[PDB]
Amino acid sequence: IPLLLFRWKPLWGEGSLEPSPQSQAEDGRSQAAVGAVPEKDTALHKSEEAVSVGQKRVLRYYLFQGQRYIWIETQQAFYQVSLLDHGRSCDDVHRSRHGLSLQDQMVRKAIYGPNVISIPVKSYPQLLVDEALNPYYGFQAFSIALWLADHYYWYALCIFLISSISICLSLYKTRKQSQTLRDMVKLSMRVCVCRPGGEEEWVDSSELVPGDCLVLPQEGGLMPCDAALVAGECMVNESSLTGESIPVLKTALPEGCAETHRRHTLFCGTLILQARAYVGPHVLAVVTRTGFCTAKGGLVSSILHPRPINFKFYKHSMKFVAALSVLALLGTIYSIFILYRNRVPLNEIVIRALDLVTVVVPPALPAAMTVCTLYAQSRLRRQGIFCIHPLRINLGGKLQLVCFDKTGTLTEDGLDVMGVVPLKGQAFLPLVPEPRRLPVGPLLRALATCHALSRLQDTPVGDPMDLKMVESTGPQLQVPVSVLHRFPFSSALQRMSVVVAWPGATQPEAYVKGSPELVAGLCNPETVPTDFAQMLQSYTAAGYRVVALASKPLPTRDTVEGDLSLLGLLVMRNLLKPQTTPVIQALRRTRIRAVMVTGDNLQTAVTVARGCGMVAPQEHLIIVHATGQPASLEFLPMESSRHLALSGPTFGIIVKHFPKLLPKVLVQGTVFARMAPEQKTELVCELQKLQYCVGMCGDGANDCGALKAADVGISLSQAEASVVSPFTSSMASIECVPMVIREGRCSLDTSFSVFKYMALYSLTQFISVLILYTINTNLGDLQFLAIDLVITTTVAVLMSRTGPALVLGRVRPPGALLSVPVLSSLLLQMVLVTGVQLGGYFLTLAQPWFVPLNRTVAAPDNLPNYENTVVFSLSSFQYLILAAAVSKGAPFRRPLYTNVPFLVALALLSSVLVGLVLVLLQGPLALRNITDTGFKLLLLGLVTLNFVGAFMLESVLDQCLPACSKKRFKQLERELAEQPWPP
Ligand SMILES: Nc1ncnc2c1ncn2[C@@H]1O[C@H](COP(=O)(O)OP(=O)(O)O)[C@@H](O)[C@H]1O
Ligand SMILES: [Mg+2]
Ligand SMILES: [Mg+2]
């Protein structure tokens, strides 16, 4: 020890590297280290090695963002604990069916931990110190001490009381955010395990390690651990990790690993429904990942350690500070040079000149910007839209592009069958609209057994496609029996296989059900006829939902899928929602681009993108359809502002073999079809590299990678807020997509209003003291208190309560404070402010009842003079004129009379402040009460010259047209104008 710099820290974290290198020795040999600093580039993080309790061997671990890193003496490095058993063979978990004994469970627990999502409950002394130990409140405690020196008790009290409001609002924001995360990871539950010889023992869910076995109750419940199913079957509701409320099917793990075997894994938190065994006495699961290593542990660990959003946090910090410093120092050296000309004794010139740098730092600035964000999150919640991080609400007003998923999002999630189109030897015999009429053969057993719905509590429950084609024929559900669901439906492979058998068969048959251009590629080519592309387009370009069916007899693996015989097409109808078409046309009107992103068929997705309005009539679009070979694009025009339509594999050829042709497609492509759930994610990440600000409105599991990758992701038709998306709407409509844009624009406008107000606020009171430091007549105590506490804090907390508009328009919020329409406002609003203070001061000098002030006493001591009363009365109205001037909401917010507490406060404070002029309270506030003539009515006729002169000045400045591209996409669009890309 003896290297601590605590003796030099009591006489003063700007540079973390220049401070930790002196408080601790720069020592190598991390086997014998105690603290580790964790970054090459980026920001620094100092981590403490933990409190190792390993008796047999020393254990050196440390938490870092929940992720334990472990020390290994045979490699001499810090490897991640999640990495440990990575690469484990598929037969090892089947040798792990008996679990772990108590001699090996305790060893495991130390390495992995208690399997708990660690949301720490911060105490109020631990949380007041986390907020008050900041430079800003360090300057506000310097301000409480500096005024107290001059005996301004009242002024000092409100610097404490405003900062106590500012602290307690940041302790409401933080404590309620962490209570939201803590209420969705609470999984205390009794769990039965198996030991090496016949034990259950009823262990707790916070006592589980990887490698341990786990039996599952028939009734089901939340999944405590990220297990792996080895023996049995179960139906899982994965709405807490994906978004689909439909149950999925979980096949047991074969013999031969968490993302590949996605249909074999029971993720943590997702509820299980039936959990049948069918092989032994009970159903077995083997634990793979625990608390911060699992998914729902890695989603929470990305919530509370987020990524920087791609928007400037108010654009300029340093530039604004520099401007303030030049502006506020030129008013500071003025009071140096003027108070010396008024012959101050130079002891009080250092306490007066340090009071001008105090008034330009308003104490209510973090409180006014906190409620600007709490009001925004509270307005979305009443409209049904939820939120986790309210720092992305301001990204809603910057959306230049929104991507949508077609089925269940633009269209209705429910289906209705139209009838099968059978096949009898390359024929396409015509459609059977009631499929309980065609005879018992391979096709009638196909659509009655190739499903995954389950008999659960008096109603069948499953996929909305599978619920309809079984209802289309109407058999009972528990004569053909299902041997094994050989392949559950995955969205990336676009098919589903079921092996069936029935009494009276020589051999079982193997049915399939998938997308028509993928099954017909798979089937024996001597069965699919020559007009399959024409018989498909006759249905799928009328707006129908078509899947195919095929069979093969079996005399397991995926030998089932291949050398099939095509049975028939199943045709379903998918109608748009009633709310889809006005929303897409509202986005197209306001120059926000809308993009179809779906996994469904191409000709179906084009006839949906016309019926709702991605492509208006008399607008040409081109289907590209690159070949699977590395040849060209071939362009097939569609006849029914260029648009483009792509297939899934077409987007794969262009991103891998035409890399310079890819930006010309993304600036004008509107329909993307047959997209894999990892190709949707790739499209969002490729659009953001063109410097778009993309949105994403989706539904279900295939959109999960795209919702995370987007700047704004919205998930539909869910309760409270899921971990999956930043914004989780619960409306089952896309009309929550303009609500986020419209709330996002007003919050980006009511934040720049509070910025302009506190700038116009500080400056007004700064000049109102500069007029009173000359003539040695500084402002009162209670007057200062009223100006800072009663007037200004009321019209800044209530200022941002207004609400967003009702109709979007094609104008964006400016996104930059220091610009020429804003500095021309702040210059010309303040030329006026000084004109009606100096002009109201030089006019009271020329009155016959006027006596000057006794200059040779002091500044605060014995002066209730006339020079204070004619300035305080004419300055206290400036804070209500400017509170309603910058609160303009005609393009973005609303007119301010809708905000009822911002009318009642702004009229009661404009009525008391008349009673301090005409009718007084002059004991307090030290007002010169001897004014008895009709000079009162001349000052009120000068306030009205400001109540009109400020509203009628910004209306001129809004009509400012200066007569005197950076974004990549804009450049491409210009190039496209000159030369069209498709021809
Ligand atoms: N339950 C199912 N069984 C078999 N095939 C399906 C099922 N659901 C969808 N498909 C087919 O798989 C393809 C891709 O699936 P998916 O991406 O989930 O489609 P969607 O965008 O309509 O949700 C679709 O063209 C659809 O025809
Ligand atoms: Mg689907
Ligand atoms: Mg969907």
Image (cartoon, rainbow, N blue to C red):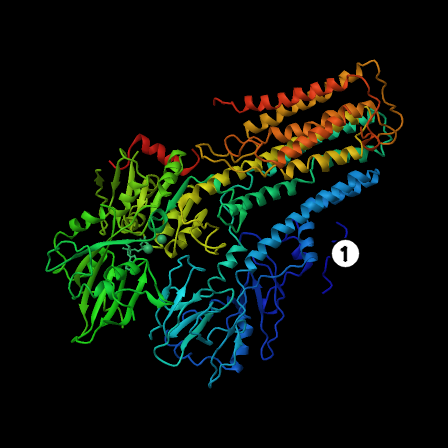
Q: Nearer the viewer, residue 380 or 55?
A: 380
- Looking at the image, which residue is at 50% across and 71% down? 75
Q: What kind of residue is marked 1?
A: Arg
Rendered view: 772 above or below 98: above
Q: Is residue 448 above or below residue 99?
A: above
Q: Is residue 330 visible?
A: no
Residue beneath the point at 68% across and 44% down: 136
Q: Nearer the viewer, residue 133 or 80?
A: 133
Which residue reaches farthest front? 458
Is 957 positioned to the left or the right of 442 in the image?
right
Quadrant position of the N terminus in the picture: bottom right
- Pinpoint residue 810: horizontal percent, then vertical percent: 43, 32
Name the residue that disc number 1 marks: 7
* Mark count: 1
Q: Residue furthest bottom?
A: 197
Q: Residue at x 33, y 73 (%)?
A: 254
Which image quarter: residue 637?
Answer: top left
Quadrant in which residue 47 is drawn? bottom right
For ligand 1, the image quadrant comes to bottom left
Residue 490 % position (x, y): 32, 61
Q: Position of residue 617 (x, y in %)?
A: 27, 35
- Residue at the location (57% across, 32% down)? 818
Spot occupied by residue 83 in the image (x, y as percentages of width and height): 46, 67
